Image (cartoon, rainbow, N blue to C red; front, side, top):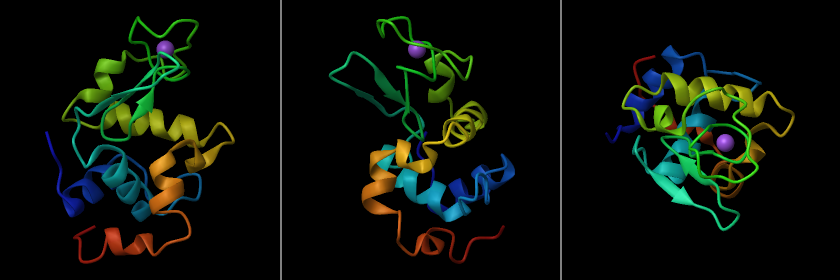
Length: 129
Ligand code: NA
């Protein structure tokens, strides 16, 4: 399913992402916009044989198991298909693990390129919660 901006803002907040690892909620909403266009089922194959999955485009190399990323880990202990669910609980859980591994949101290219050092507050502007 495809989220709207404030709809995603609430869903990420609900799931503990406001200010997690010190990333304001807007960073996360921003990230998803440019990672997945807010679509919970976005996948994007990488040349290294991994795939990015879901609203936050979590990668199979380290974070989720999709059973076809050679020599990979599953550090969020989830199948990559959990990250494609309309319910973003697993995606957010996993993203929290990613930013907690010392790479922070630099893990996500679209954050680095379209959110970091920007007015990410704009992505939550006018939202209830
Ligand atoms: Na994996």
